[PDB]
Amino acid sequence: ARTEKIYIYGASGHGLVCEDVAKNMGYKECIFLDDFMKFESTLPKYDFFIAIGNNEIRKKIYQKISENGFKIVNLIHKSALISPSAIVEENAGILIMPYVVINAKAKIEKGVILNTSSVIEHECVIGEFSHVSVGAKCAGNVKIGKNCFLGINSCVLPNLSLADDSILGGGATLVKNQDEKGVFVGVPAKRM
Amino acid sequence: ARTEKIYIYGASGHGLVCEDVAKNMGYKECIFLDDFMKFESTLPKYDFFIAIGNNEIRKKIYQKISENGFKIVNLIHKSALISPSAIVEENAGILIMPYVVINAKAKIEKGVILNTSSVIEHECVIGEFSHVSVGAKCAGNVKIGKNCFLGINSCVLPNLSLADDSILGGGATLVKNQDEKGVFVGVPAKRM
Amino acid sequence: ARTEKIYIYGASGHGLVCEDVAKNMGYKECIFLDDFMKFESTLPKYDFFIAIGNNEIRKKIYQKISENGFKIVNLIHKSALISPSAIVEENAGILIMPYVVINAKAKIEKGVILNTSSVIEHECVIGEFSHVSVGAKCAGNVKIGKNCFLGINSCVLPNLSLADDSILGGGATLVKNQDEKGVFVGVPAKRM
Ligand SMILES: CNc1nc(CCc2ccccc2)nc2sc(C(=O)O)c(C)c12
Ligand SMILES: CNc1nc(CCc2ccccc2)nc2sc(C(=O)O)c(C)c12
Ligand SMILES: CNc1nc(CCc2ccccc2)nc2sc(C(=O)O)c(C)c12
Image 1 (cartoon, rainbow over the protein chains, first blue to last red):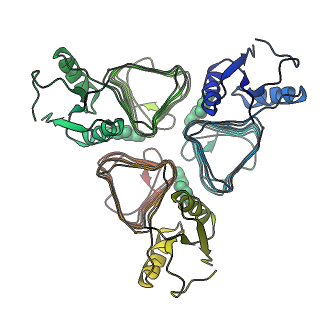
Image 2: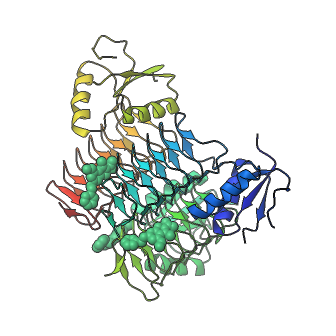
Image 3: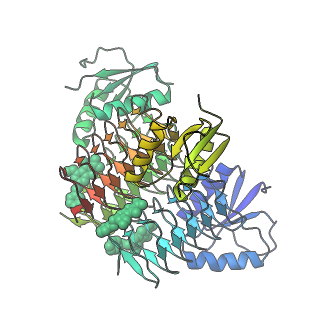
């Protein structure tokens, strides 16, 4: 079950958006924790979510909050369509925004952000603490490494792999594998 | 409340699409006014909508029809997802198409068109009589000026501002501020 | 009506996705036929679908299966929004994925794939056995020829026509007519 209330850590734009998704799930109230009220392990053990966009910082908090013993839940909007054979790591800090689609046998690891109207096609693997931005789309069988960032309206052709800690620019179209980390921009996306 | 019938002004493709949205809202019938039957202030005071894509012309009509005393309503498809803290100017000629998403504290001014599957992220401001085309996406905290046109599948990176009367080309990815008006195309979008 | 069961021909990623759409429609069970169990005309006459992405091969099978007397149905996800005045050829092997939008008076011919979150605007014509990929968008009054392939996140400006057997690259933005076949890539899309 879910608690009646939920802690949203982060009070900037991303947090307001997470507040909307949590309410859509039926949480009656969001208690924002400042990120800049303040956090300590003694708070009533409500469900928890880290509403910080930056992958590295979100991860360091996630590491903290877990060790302090809170359940970092997933915030999944009801309008997200998720194949029954897709796997989304449970109680793993994952945000899935409105009108996201995740298709057959895709895997979403912990800490991932799947932002508004993004698409994860069949058989993809989205590595932990990745951020698939607004409208970004992975064709089938794509491997997104840990801590990757796919910019707004970017896309990845099918059967491609993107190395851990890479950034795909807003609007960029990735058409080849990238085994070493980098920043890739344009159509086709090129190392920048 | 809404009247049982609604005037759709414009009989081209955009008008047929507005007819679909008005019916989705539950209007029982759309009475098309020619734009090329003809309009005069004496018609029964049904709800009204200007189904003209061009921002300048839509605005001049809007100016007319209001002064003649008709309520120019908003046509909002039921599948649009609109944050409770987003503000959409009421009875202000705004069209919101299927699967549009408008997130926390965004503001949509009068006369705007938000076309199919477009995305207005949190805290954006879309200036009056703008047209955000099919699939076009504004990241968070974007300011779109009055009478702007964002082309199909274009996008704007977060915290950017686009000057009044600018055009962002189809497919273009805007990555920097643009304080003076222009036509911007490509990935990254460049002054054309 | 639809039969209780349906044959899905093709057992790769595309087939798993078609299995999801068929179930969403309420088929109780998908019987996969190997494409590599095996097919012959004597099987119980359940509804049939060709879950092969390649346009040429899908067509040759479609030609076969029809001549063997099976009804090749359409698989249309419930979350697809299809104008009442749009025409989708019935029992014509058409796949329409989640969150697809087809607007007023558009026409979808037999064998077309409209993949996840794609958009077919008003008055378009999508020619038979075309594949409009993930997130690809046709503005209003676009003519897509037979056996065309529009890549992930590509788009076509309004009132354009694309010649039979053309390919529009992933991410590409087509801004001019193309009366002779080709492969078009980039923003703007250029012959490659
Ligand atoms: C510096 N910030 C960014 N930079 C680029 C790449 C810009 C670029 C550079 C050169 C060519 C094309 C694009 N894309 C994106 S997407 C994005 C988001 O919220 O989706 C952000 C914040 C960025
Ligand atoms: C001339 N009409 C247009 N021009 C361009 C820009 C074309 C361009 C030029 C150079 C490089 C890239 C793109 N985009 C768009 S979007 C669009 C729509 O309904 O979304 C239209 C009617 C246009
Ligand atoms: C070779 N396969 C592809 N190639 C290109 C074009 C790559 C390109 C080349 C040069 C410039 C830009 C893009 N687009 C796409 S979309 C796509 C899909 O499932 O949507 C595929 C399988 C491809």
